[PDB]
Amino acid sequence: QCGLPKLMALELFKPFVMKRLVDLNHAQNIKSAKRMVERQRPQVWDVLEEVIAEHPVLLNRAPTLHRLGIQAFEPQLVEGKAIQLHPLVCEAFNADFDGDQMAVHLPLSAEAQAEARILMLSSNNILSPASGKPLAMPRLDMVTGLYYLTTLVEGATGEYQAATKDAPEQGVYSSPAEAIMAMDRGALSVRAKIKVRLTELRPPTDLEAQLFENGWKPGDAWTAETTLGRVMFNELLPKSYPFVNEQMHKKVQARIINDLAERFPMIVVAQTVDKLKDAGFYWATRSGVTVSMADVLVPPQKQEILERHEAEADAIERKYQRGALNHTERNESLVKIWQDATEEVGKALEEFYPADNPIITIVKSGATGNLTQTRTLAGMKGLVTNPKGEFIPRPIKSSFREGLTVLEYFINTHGARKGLADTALRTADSGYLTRRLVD
Amino acid sequence: SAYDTPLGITNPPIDELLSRASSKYALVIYAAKRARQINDYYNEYVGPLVEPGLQEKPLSIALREIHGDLLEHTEG
Amino acid sequence: MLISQRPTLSEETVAENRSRFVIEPLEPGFGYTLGNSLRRTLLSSIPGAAVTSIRIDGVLHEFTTVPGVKEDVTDIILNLKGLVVSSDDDEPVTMYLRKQGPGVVTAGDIVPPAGVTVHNPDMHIATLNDKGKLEVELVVERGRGYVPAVQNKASGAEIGRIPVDSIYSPVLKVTYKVEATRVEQRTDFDKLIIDVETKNSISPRDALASAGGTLVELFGLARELNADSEHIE
Amino acid sequence: MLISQRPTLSEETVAENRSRFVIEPLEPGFGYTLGNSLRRTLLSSIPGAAVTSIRIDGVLHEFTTVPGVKEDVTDIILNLKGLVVSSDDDEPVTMYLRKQGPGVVTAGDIVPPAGVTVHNPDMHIATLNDKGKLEVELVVERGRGYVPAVQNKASGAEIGRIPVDSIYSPVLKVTYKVEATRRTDFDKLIIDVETKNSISPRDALASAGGTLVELFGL
Amino acid sequence: WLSAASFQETTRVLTDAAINCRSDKLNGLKENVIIGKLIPAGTGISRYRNIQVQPTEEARAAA
Amino acid sequence: CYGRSMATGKLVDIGEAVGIVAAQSIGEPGTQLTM
Amino acid sequence: IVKGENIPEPGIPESFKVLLKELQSLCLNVEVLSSDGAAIEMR
Amino acid sequence: LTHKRRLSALGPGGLSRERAGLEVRDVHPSHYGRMCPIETPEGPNIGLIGSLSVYARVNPFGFIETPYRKVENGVVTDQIDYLTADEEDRHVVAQANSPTDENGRFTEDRVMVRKKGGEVEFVSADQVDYMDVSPRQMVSVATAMIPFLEHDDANRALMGANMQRQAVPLVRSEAPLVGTGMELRAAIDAGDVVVADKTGVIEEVSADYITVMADDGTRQSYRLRKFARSNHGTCANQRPIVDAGQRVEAGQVIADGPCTQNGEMALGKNLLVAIMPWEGHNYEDAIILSNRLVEEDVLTSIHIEEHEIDARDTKLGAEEITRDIPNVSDEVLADLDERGIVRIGAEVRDGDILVGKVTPKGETELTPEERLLRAIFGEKAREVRDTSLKVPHGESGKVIGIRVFSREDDDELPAGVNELVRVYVAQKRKISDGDKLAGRHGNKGVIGKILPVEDMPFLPDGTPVDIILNTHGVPRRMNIGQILETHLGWVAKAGWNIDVAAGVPDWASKLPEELYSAPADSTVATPVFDGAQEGELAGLLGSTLPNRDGEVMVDADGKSTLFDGRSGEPFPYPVTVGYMYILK
């Protein structure tokens, strides 16, 4: 589906609604029908919903790179003048909500609508027709939203205690619906290690063999130890699918969704990814993931590492200032001294950040971000290239958390501009190539 | 197989439809020409062999007919 | 004052245990406002009876095991947690289940004292291995909501007394979500969808009216203040 | 473990415009869901009175100025949006404001018709000079929520009438909080209701309840 | 020839095509796009577009 | 000879035009090729 | 669409007709030929 | 103001478009203090267009000069010498910020220096000649207006500058809560603000004009632009900031321009921000807003159109502007006056008539079916076709003013044009879903949803946050200034008091002068490279704590516990809240 501004939809379908409201007594002749739509008499809207029903439309966003750049959807009248786009198709369209626009086309002939619903329908195209990998697979929020749900926390609230002596195990629940009643109260934590009895879910292949081996369990109860979230996670997958019981990285979700397309019909993956979306968002907001000057940490070893390599350069600079050193090797020595010195801060930085820090969880789960990106935010930004392409031996010691200096900022722009200019002519050339490949 | 319930355009599922035709392309002309047939009736002449929905569009009808194996075709 | 569109409460039956209910149309954003309040009233607000503590013969200082049966201590505790019995007492009552027969024990084997009625006799409790006996006492006290197993410092006085997690309310699962309706007349009005899976003690419709009444009366505390402002039906 | 002492709602006072309200006792995990259920209803459906349109003699529309007045007509209507009025009468009732000579016009200078009151006459509207004269009438209606200005082409209004965004919201700011327990442990919530002075925190909370009670049905 | 023309070096292509007196059978899909024909691919192929559809005699009975 | 259709997961359909799909599949990532 | 009839079969794009004309103005003789039917006219 | 001051390499007499090599686009070392490296276009024009720097100055020969303070023997004098790029490489440039010694001298053991390479080196301060006049010499006016510039990557900064010039004047025009130095100085030099050129007192203040009685006995007066449609449609309206008896001084601000408040540039509003991801509604750069921003017209802005139609001399007759239209209902003309032009103050809808016009026709040859109806209903076929000015598709508003130029009346017109009428329509545009908002750091996004103030993340006060920004796009884009000013934005809003217990805490050692206390709502300024530092932030994070009652609403991490307005329960983790300056 897609959100279609009601004004836009009225004009697109204007000839259709004109006939429908003349068929009904609303308008006596086509002339009246035309004016009735132009001035937007309130009667048309109930008519528009009928014509639009199960009548697809094509949505394009330029530039169109692969055929996935055009996809059919079922229109839904929406309030406002903007267009509502499903969050899973942003990957194919390369669509940012920074203010991009999209085009709508109305297939008319029976054949055109057939091709829309069948060939180009949104849910039928999931994997990219290049690598076969899944595209509509969740990303960004939905990643960190699920990664939080499935993750297992040691010493959480209500954790199964493996009780001894005077008390029974204490970590068991009659059913999942009980773990929810325990979660609503402060008893249970969604990330807890407790073990539950599950009637409606399927155990893993291995354990299913030892447990039953006479068949599988639609109603047959079995017990495993998993986080309450991992339970709810597997309720999103098909009832026939085995219990994964893992914390979901992006690649792990790729493995799973990739597998569903082999063992299950398209319509099944279409609905399973819809369910991952709703779940991922809900937990993305409950994830408690924000940013702050506090949540940005810098390693205390940065001072010693920095001042240490400084003398190593000053000594090599003293060796070059002594006349013996080769000028080309001097900078090369500095470039090597500082290059791997950045790795140390990167190593020290990772050691410092608690695994639950919101900045790293974003990169860990594979939702978005890189480590090289979080290395310039805190710690050091590193060396920057000169205009000629050579590496400026003067490193940037400060990080964008502490802020750069007057000269540090002027130097970074030297490189930062060359990169942004490249992206300019990288699209113009890449498109000229594609035009020759196509021909 | 339980896919739950498809809504509107997604019903019937393509998987159940593709077993009734050689490819996704053949399926297109299949339902396409039949829908063009239905609309002529409301003005070839035959169908709606199934029970028409309330306002249901003829193309949507022809899709349900192919799902029920109510018609057959022969490729050129 | 206020006169609005008349909402309609409907019920779709998924099974004898479950039913789906929908309210249409609401006024925006009222769907979200009363929705979470209903999931709480149905879950924690309905009076019901449930098992509190249990003691079984043969387990005192033992950690987990029961020679003579294939069900462990843990598996039987959560096996009894599903027992559904409506007790009219307003005070704890101790039922008893004693069987030495090498066969399957069920909820029907327990003798309820006068005033307590077991609604799920078919429930399996334990499988007795050949030539073995099973003796169990059960504490049943009326309550509301979900009360986790409580060791009160008086649970350490009893030797072999196992406090268990008590499900007091008949509804073991509930959830809700909102949707938009009203093609033209109303624009983007709210529709409330609520899912109720109820125990055999009470049907879904009765749990609703019980939650409806307990909820309506609760807001009377404010309305009694004045009654000046109003709405319509 | 049935524990019954029927919920008790006791009043209080903090300021004149706002007063706390407390309700105890309640089952665990309640006051949150119950508080936000009132707050959601307080901030929206509390009925009230507000000015719909306005008519100024010299000006035929919103974007001009008035001779001698320091505020343009658009910046005067911005000020007039701050008027808190209460109309005890159904149907539209027009107020009147006329001022000459220097001075500073304020909401108090508006002459309320029968059964209508300006509850913050201290409000600044426009500063007039010796040449400045301001003659304007105001139409007060009754409603709830926020209704965007109704265009006179949609109504039967004439080119002279200036429609304005109307906010009927007696309530101002609202919050709550709960005291849990850990004898069995119950929950008790306390709510803080503040109003614009067109009504007291009591009549508002009674409005929500009276409006919230009628909604729940079975 | 008209597929090579629209691609690049139009003037060069046309001068050599008119001297060689070339004939374009309009088989390629770009040619059919220019003149508004059905591209010889997908649903445009002969076997697919010539499909004939009629309801089964058993179905016409049920009416 | 061609093999499974990456989009379908099954043997390619007879109508498919793999030339264009190939060209696009090669070019589309070109924006990510540093140079 | 206004009569609820079936959408008809497409015609010849006017732009293409203009192409043949612009090619003729270059002293290029462009003839649209039938299978066995020799020359065709656009009119 | 940035259009002027812009310098480009294009046009006749220079390399044009593709011809230019990419080496020119690269920033040279001599662009320091002359051409701003950070401000340029993002598109194919990168590096060919740039804005003159702040202190830069043009030479009578056409070479840009930059101001410097010459240093002699480790002492920086008050002598300021403007130097061309040629003579700069000859000397060594000390760094703008270096420790200052008493009456002045170089305190640091070594001094930052710039060589002809350029090359960065040190000496003992003995060999330095000239020093920088101050930080942000290289920066332009727009670039210098980005708070916490030093923290943001050049990529997102360039986007930040370009998007300030894309803002639009609002009706209220509130100034930035956390600013920089340029806000006031740039507004007056723009020319859109009313400045007084002689000391005196105010005789009168009206929406129309403001008159001042100088000490000189002379009398100056200023007519205020009111709702003047700008080139691109933005509203140019001005408002008087002074009262009748006020004293004033030469060069003061009498009235505010479109985007200015009290003399300094206001390109947007200050809003309560929440950095939690929220129910998938703000995702992939999308944004959500409090419906308060609608009801209270905080983001509302005015836009004005100019429609034009002429009546000329046709070979078949003369065009006539008239209320008579060949076929129309008497209703479609309801808003037209005698002459056929829309009546001032009317509302217009897409397709509505503005100026009725008619042109002569030539032999009609009506269709037989058209002539039969003419006889039946007796409507005589008119001699003139209807060419009439109507409002464009998807456009509506109120009629502000009309301008009519007639030939009868002398006026002036090109040969053949008898009458020309222009109609000006204006409309109030509320902030709507789909509109594009952004901050000064390059962060941009459409409004994805607008929620009732009822259900919004809201502080324990009961104070709903106005905007909710997603957390994911923040870390990777390398603009962390938005978070900083989000914290400081909350500082300046609620005030603060540094502890007077004992002495001054260690974080204030080198730090603010009599900034130890500020009231609530006080405005802050952090010059780009001289601005506040991380240590001083934290120290301020803990700070004065009313709302009304004495409870703190934000911790020293810049976080608070927000209550979901839908379910009514707190959000599990502390969420960062604050005030950020966002532009429409």
Image (cartoon, coloured by chain):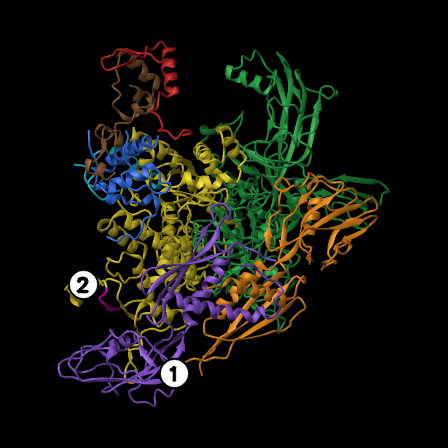
Chain colours: A yellow, B blue, C purple, D orange, E brown, F cyan, G red, H green
- Residue under the image location 80 percent in, 40 percent down: H220
Assign a secondary structure to mark 1: loop
Q: Amino acid at mark 1?
A: Asp
Mark 2 and mark 1: Cα distance apart in space: 48 Å
Residue A392 as seen in the image, left or right of residue H78: left
Depth check: give the residue in front, C65 or A247: C65
Residue C58 as seen in the image, left or right of residue H339: left
**Residue range of the region highlighted in magenta in the rendering:** A219-224
- Can residue A416 be seen here? The reply is yes
List the residue tagged with mark 2: A206
- Front position among marks 2 and 1: 1
How many numbered circles does the render carry? 2
Give percent across and percent down for residue A201: 26, 62
Give percent across and percent down for residue H574: 48, 64
The quarter of the picture where residue D144 lies is bottom right
Q: Amino acid at mark 2?
A: Asp
- Residue under the image location 63 percent in, 51 percent down: D166
Residue D195 as seen in the image, left or right of residue A164: right
In the rendered view of the protein, which quadrant contains the C terminus of chain H?
top right
Badge 1 sits on which subunit? C
Image: H43 above or below H76: above
Give percent across and percent down for residue C75: 24, 75
Residue H391 as seen in the image, left or right of residue A401: right
Badge 2 sits on which subunit? A
Image: A69 above or below E52: below
Depth check: give the residue in front, E61 or B60: E61
- Can residue F35 be seen here? The reply is no
Give percent across and percent down for residue H371: 54, 16
Residue placed furthest toward the right = H217
Assign a secondary structure to mark 2: helix
List the residue tagged with mark 1: C89
